[PDB]
Length: 50
Length: 50
Image (tube, each protein chain N blue to C red):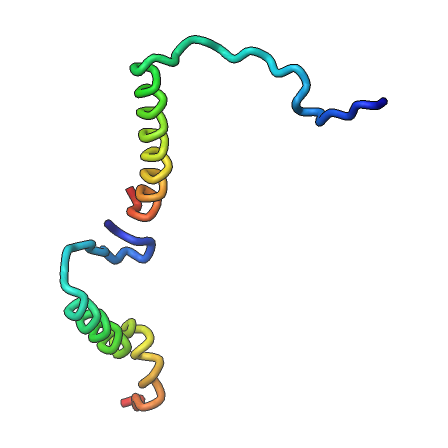
């Protein structure tokens, strides 16, 4: 017989095991919130001439 | 904050109807406000030489 397999399913590498505690998850959530504020502030600053 | 033309724009908390009526009145009156050199050009053909 013959076997055909999707290319992207071949041998996934192990993912990291660090920065998965509750504190690290808060850090990622905090970073996303403050990163969004950076984009909006740049817009607001542009529209306010300041 | 100031704009490019030198005008100052104020962003305040105000009612919708008052803002709409006030802004429209400003547009109508500003039609009859012209530069002095523009006024002189309009009436330059009515000035005698005496």
